[PDB]
Amino acid sequence: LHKEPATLIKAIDGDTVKLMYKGQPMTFRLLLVDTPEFNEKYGPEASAFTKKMEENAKKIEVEFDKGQRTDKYGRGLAYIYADGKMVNEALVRQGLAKVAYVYKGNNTHEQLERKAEAQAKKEKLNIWS
Ligand SMILES: Cc1cn([C@H]2C[C@H](OP(=O)(O)O)[C@@H](COP(=O)(O)O)O2)c(=O)[nH]c1=O
Ligand SMILES: [Ca+2]
Image (cartoon, rainbow, N blue to C red; front, side, top):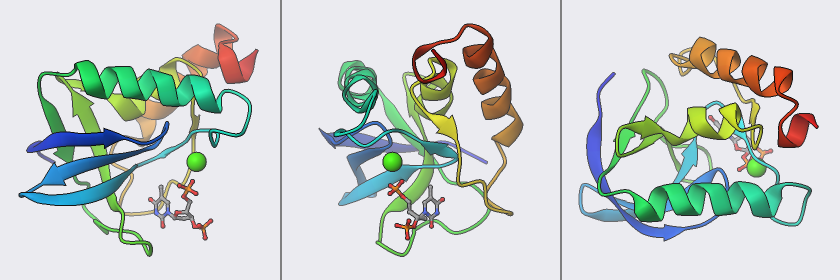
């Protein structure tokens, strides 16, 4: 896999973000995670966490996996990086997302995510408290 440039257009919530990619506005859905909706427990905390990560980043990058690059709603499916740090993984490590939606052929960072989740669970963070 490789990283490609993008720029933030707007934060949305824990696991979606509006980015400009190849010069076109797109909503991205983060691979391999599920954050609570804003109206649910830890929804607001997940959204704040990603908003800060994405807004403070000097450089946003997107990394597509091997499989489908857009979902049935037209959202881009990617791993998103904020100054080199993967948002998908950080969410999970902080107990603000669950590893989820792991489909065959778009699961390159699965074990990375699961290791983070195991550590969040051990620390009883947030969702796991
Ligand atoms: C993360 C992800 C979600 N999706 C689809 C499956 C779910 O369909 P349904 O909408 O029919 O439940 C939906 C969940 O996204 P949200 O968690 O953003 O709601 O997005 C994919 O198709 N591929 C993916 O990699
Ligand atoms: Ca969600």
